[PDB]
Image (cartoon, coloured by chain):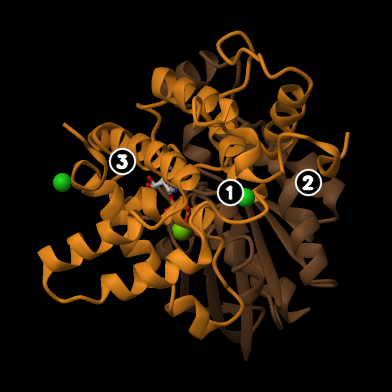
């Protein structure tokens, strides 16, 4: 009934992944569905999902981890929203707070190439479980951006509509707000330059 | 006379376009000003624009303090956005802005009769929000009033801000 009692949502990331299956099943299910049916949706991740239906999707998944989205009648923004809820309900943000500090330091490097190399070095410091899921989500967002002539979601727009879900920022004052402009830029860079950060030949 | 207006509602439901009429870029935090004359009174209306994404739920309370009137929006081509009025927006606004008048605004009225919109919503077994459905929701949440507008055609836009101003002044 209530989300506190779920053994899947609101529990540590490490408890819903394994070395063998590093992507949470729910995240794989949502993202595969969105890639199959949602890449041409104008404003995917910008347009708000149906909150009631998002919660319903989560509860139905709780009841059955083998839930079939192709079979159900949840719309794409509901699936996108429920996917965001997984990350916002994690005990700690997908990008750990200590890593965010290091990312902000790296981002201040003036030399572009040095900056990108520095940011990649910070990635190697993520916990391995977080790194794999972060890679998976950013790579998905990069694929969404490839269709931006149709869905209008550039890497900039995707960052604006997803980075707080990943980082869980302090929004408690105006000065705190301006201090978040770097977070938006950093996630935009990870999305836009996904190949540099995450491909392996 | 200075009055503060805050606009809220689902991402991409047309908030900024509504303010501006008085690009595809989501708002995080912006402020505008409009001058309105209603009932012999001249009001300088501060327009506080907000982000509709749940990503910015913890940021929105920065805009709510000392608000005189709320524009609470949904889009007429999005029945999801209407369902989010009682589910999300009304609880939030009434939590942070007790005794602040709410104008319930149905945006994008031009899409109600739009063949493309109706064809695309049909594929999802949906259809545009009906005027009665909007009015009933306004009644349900105890809104100051209900208004439909199209920022694209300008239909009803002036009327929205006059009503918002009268609400603020009263
Ligand atoms: N057809 C139509 N489209 C609109 C209207 N108002 C806004 N839009 C479109 O809706 C999208 C998002 O609008 P915007 O005002 O930025 O949304 P918000 O600030 O996120 O609520 C943009 O593509 C706008 O062009 C309208 O009255 N009619
Ligand atoms: Cl965690
Ligand atoms: Cl690259
Ligand atoms: Mg806006």
Disc 2 chain ID: B
Chain identifier, colour brown:
B
Where B34 falls versus A167 (above or below)?
Answer: below
Which percent across, then down, holds residue B37?
A: 57, 79
Please report contact status of discs 1 and 3: CB closer than 8 Å, yes or no: no
Where B80 falls versus A28 (above or below)?
Answer: below
Q: Would you call the spot at circle 2 few (<14 residues within 10 Å), some (14-19), or many (20 or more)?
A: some
Q: Are the numbered discs 2 and 3 placed on the same chain, yes or no?
A: no
Q: CA distance from mark 1 to mark 3?
A: 17 Å
Residue at 36% of width from left, 27% of height from top? A39
Q: CA distance from mark 1 to mark 2?
A: 12 Å
Which percent across, then down, holds residue B65?
A: 70, 81
Closest to the observer, A17 or A94: A17
Chain identifier, colour orange:
A
- Identify the residue position indicated by label 3 in the image: A152
Q: CA distance from mark 2 to mark 3?
A: 29 Å
Disc 1 Cβ-to-ligand 1 distance below 8 Å: yes
Helix, strand or loop status at disc 1: loop
Helix, strand or loop status at disc 3: loop
- Identify the residue position indicated by label 2 in the image: B86
Residue B10 is tagged as: 1
Which percent across, then down, holds residue A70?
A: 55, 11
Closest to the observer, B49 or A175: A175
Helix, strand or loop status at disc 2: helix
Q: Are the numbered discs 1 and 3 placed on the same chain, yes or no?
A: no
């Amino acid at each position: 009934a209530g989300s506190w009692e779920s053994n899947y949502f609101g529990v540590p990331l490490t408890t819903v992944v394994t070395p063998e299956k590093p992507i949470p099943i729910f995240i794989e299910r949502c993202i595969e569905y969105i890639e199959a049916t949602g890449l041409s949706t104008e404003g995917i991740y910008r347009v708000s999902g149906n909150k009631s239906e998002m919660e319903s999707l989560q509860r139905q998944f709780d009841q059955d981890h083998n839930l079939d989205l192709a079979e159900k009648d949840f719309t794409v923004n509901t699936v996108a929203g429920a996917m965001k809820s997984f990350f916002s309900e994690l005990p700690d943000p997908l990008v750990p707070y200590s890593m965010q500090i290091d990312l902000v330091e790296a981002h201040k490097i003036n030399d572009r190439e040095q900056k990108l190399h520095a940011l990649k070095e910070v990635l190697k410091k993520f916990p391995k479980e977080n790194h794999e899921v972060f890679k998976y989500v950013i790579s998905h967002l990069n694929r969404v951006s490839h269709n931006n002539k149709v869905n209008l979601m550039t890497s900039e727009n995707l960052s604006i509509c997803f980075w707080p879900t990943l980082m869980r920022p302090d929004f408690s004052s105006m000065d705190a707000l301006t201090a978040t402009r770097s977070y938006q830029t950093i996630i935009e860079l990870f999305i836009q330059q996904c190949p540099f950060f995450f491909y392996n030949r | 006379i200075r009055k503060k207006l805050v606009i809220v509602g689902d991402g991409a439901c047309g908030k900024t376009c509504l303010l501006i009429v008085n690009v595809y870029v989501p708002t995080v935090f912006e402020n505008y000003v409009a001058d309105i004359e209603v009932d012999g009174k001249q009001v300088e209306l501060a327009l506080w624009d907000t982000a509709g994404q749940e990503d910015y739920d913890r940021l929105r309370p920065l805009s709510y303090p000392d608000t005189d009137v709320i524009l609470m929006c949904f889009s007429i081509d999005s029945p999801d956005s209407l369902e989010n009025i009682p589910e999300k927006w009304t609880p939030e606004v009434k939590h942070f802005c007790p005794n602040v008048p709410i104008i319930l605004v149905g945006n994008k009225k031009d899409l109600r009769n739009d063949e493309h919109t109706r064809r695309e919503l049909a594929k999802m077994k949906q259809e545009p929000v009906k005027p009665e459905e909007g009015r009933d929701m306004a009644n349900r949440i105890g809104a100051f009033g209900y208004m439909e507008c199209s920022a694209k055609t300008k239909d009803g836009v002036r009327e929205v801000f006059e009503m918002a101003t009268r609400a603020a002044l009263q």
